[PDB]
Amino acid sequence: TKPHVNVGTIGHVDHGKSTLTAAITKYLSLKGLAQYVPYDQIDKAPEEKARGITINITHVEYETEKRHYAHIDCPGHADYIKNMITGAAQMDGAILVVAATDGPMPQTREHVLLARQVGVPYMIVFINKTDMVDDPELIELVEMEVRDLLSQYEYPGDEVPVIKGSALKALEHEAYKPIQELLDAMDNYIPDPQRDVDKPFLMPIEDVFSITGRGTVVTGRIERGRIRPGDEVEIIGLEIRKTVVTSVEMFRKELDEGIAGDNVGCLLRGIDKDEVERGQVLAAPGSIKPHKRFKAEVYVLKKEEGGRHTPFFKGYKPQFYIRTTDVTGEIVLPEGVEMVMPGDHVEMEIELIYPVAIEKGQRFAIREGGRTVGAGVVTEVIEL
Ligand SMILES: Nc1nc2c(ncn2[C@@H]2O[C@H](COP(=O)(O)OP(=O)(O)O)[C@@H](O)[C@H]2O)c(=O)[nH]1
Ligand SMILES: [Mg+2]
Image (cartoon, rainbow, N blue to C red; front, side, top):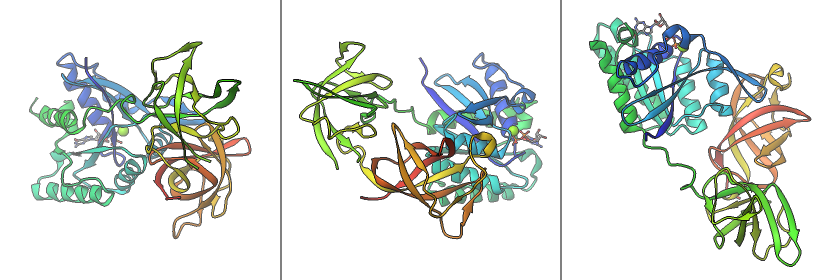
């Protein structure tokens, strides 16, 4: 059975993302490896909802002989902003489409920035529209500039695969080679995703209660990794404490192990009922640390998406929903940024009133009153 990998086409509008997506499904349909989805159906993307946010996004699926790919493609720049920050459809690798004619453009830069900010681990470049460029040295110019763009945002720009071709020619036989070259790069450059159960154990604590004569139980849904009776864990958030999970219980049965997705109850050895609380996390020791201060790429929701008309500003103190708890925090904006209007995104500095377990790449909501006013992805954690 083939591993499932999430990918998507990013880049500036009209550079050929939707055309490349169609060409991939057509090329693979000829080998019985994909449903052919024509360009018109990919381009007219349907709507879907990430909580109150509506995003236009096309999902298609196709297989190489080795892999099953889940592929996303969006019409508008705003769709990519919302999809990448809210994590509606996450990506193991991004296919950066850059037209060789006009070359890299504002959304080329911004989508690379967003990919880095949201933690997309690998980039593959497809230089499109080469059928329109007669001077081959100018195609190399575009490649070099895209490589420098990736390096500017800490991607290994010298090492990423860069495929040149014409998505349109492929969509209309020798023009299939860039498609095959692209798929081989996806097969070889993007590694098989490590699955949640080999990741370090983490479970946010939802509820705490005491069994008299036995000890303190914390309940929560395991986010990643495994927990087994006898394992050592740390309680992170709000001074770090070590303990042993004596027992893992789910559906009135003691488990040999709890895995990601299991809502379990963990009996904590020697933990007083008043010293652990909702919002802390159980974690494999050393795998995550408490922080009061961190940076995060934050999208400010529009009023129509459930947010407010008011922008974010220096000193704004909303609530930060970090896993199972919400904590007051104070906003600081980067240099030269005085406000963030709804619909915009920026990297903000956040200082919570008390430390919580938080890590790079973690997503969180920002709420003010009853409205969700922002969505963020942690980009940096600051030492306590
Ligand atoms: N000449 C040429 N035109 C292309 C190529 N790929 C796409 N186009 C034209 O792209 C216009 C926009 O590209 P499209 O895929 O719809 O947009 P995108 O998904 O927003 O980048 C249409 O004319 C596409 O057919 C190509 O490889 N060569
Ligand atoms: Mg498109």
